[PDB]
Amino acid sequence: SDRNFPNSTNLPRNPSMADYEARIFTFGTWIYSVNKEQLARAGFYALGEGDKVKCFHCGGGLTDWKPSEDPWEQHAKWYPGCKYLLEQKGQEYINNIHLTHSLEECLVR
Amino acid sequence: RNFPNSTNLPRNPSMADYEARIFTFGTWIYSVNKEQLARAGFYALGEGDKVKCFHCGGGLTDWKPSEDPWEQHAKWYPGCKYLLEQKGQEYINNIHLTHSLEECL
Ligand SMILES: [Zn+2]
Ligand SMILES: [Zn+2]
Image (cartoon, rainbow over all chains, first blue to last red; front, side, top):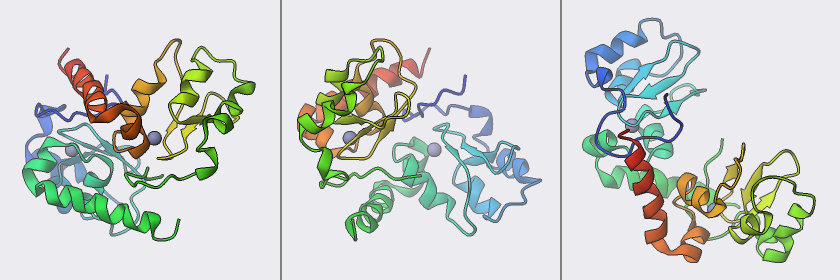
């Protein structure tokens, strides 16, 4: 189905990609300019069409990576409720990416 | 993009008062209640069923018949500060726990 609504429980949506090495493999043909090792470690595998990656745990998708963007920071911006993210980076990171993004908000606006 | 605001100050302070909002829905002709949407912070964008919350800047589209507008506001923009002020935290969480029940079917 790959429903739009992400997965903020602990059961990894696509469990067949819970392995790291299974993921960096999907970046075999990766031409885009974000670091693929930093990518997979952040929980992403490549969908093989364009630059679309999905997360293996929350099923969250990302596109149009601007060059040298951080997979980790990006993961937490759009899906602040991913359990594997919470596992890896811990709440403050998640609250920080958001806190700074709530800042260049009102900074002028 | 872009990033909806978890922040406390609204994004379109002009669509703050209810009366300004329902005015967008003067033409509105969809199977979703117009007077419910406006109550929920939303204003019509003119094109399609596309509506937007005045406070967070969330946009919702492809509406289905009888879909509760309050529910969706919570579903897609939980960090919305106006939503919170109108429904309390618990309500928002109920929607998320109910859709996490879906996650195992
Ligand atoms: Zn995730
Ligand atoms: Zn809102």
